[PDB]
Image (cartoon, rainbow, N blue to C red; front, side, top):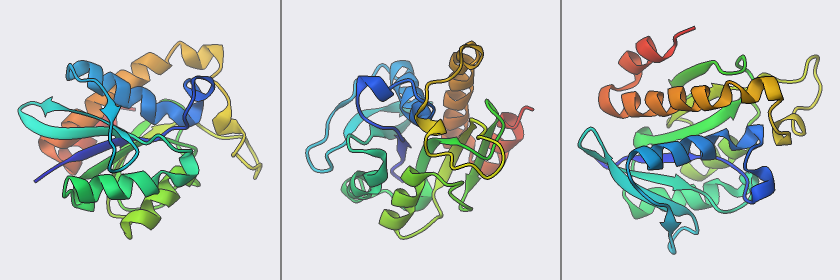
Length: 189
C-alpha cells in the first residue's frame, strides 16, 4: 500500500526555525537520508520528495501554504497517490509533551495544533499516524499560539538536531514495523 509522510510548518525563511516548523525540519532530514530533493507538486500545491526506506517506497511532503490550510494540500496529496489515512504519517510539534519527548499514535486529539485540525478536517478522520515531538507550552492556561511561532531557546537549540534525528528514526521505524513495535523502541524516556 502507498505511504505518505508529511511534515507540518509555515512557509518562509523567517519561520523555518520556529517550534511550529519541527515537522519541516524532520522532513528535510528524511529527504537528506533518502538522497531525495523536494520538487513542486502541481496537483496539490505542496512540494514532494520520493524515495525508499528499507526498500519500501514513500512520498515525503511539505505543504506550501500557511499552517492553517495544511489539509487543503494534504487531502489532495492523499487522493493523488491513493494513500489511505491509516498510511499517512504526520510529523508535528506537540504542546502537550515535554520538550524533546517523542511519542507515536494513531487517532486521538490534536493537542491544539491548528495544522492537525486542518488535516483531520480534510481527511474526514483522526485515524492517521502521528510523530509527536514535544515542545512544552506556556504555564497556566495561557494561549500557546504565539509560543509556537517563536524560535527555540539557545539551550533548546543544543538538543534540537538530536531530537530531529530521533524523530526521523521514529518515522522510519513506523514505516518498517508499525505502531506498537515502533512505540516500544521510540518512547525512550
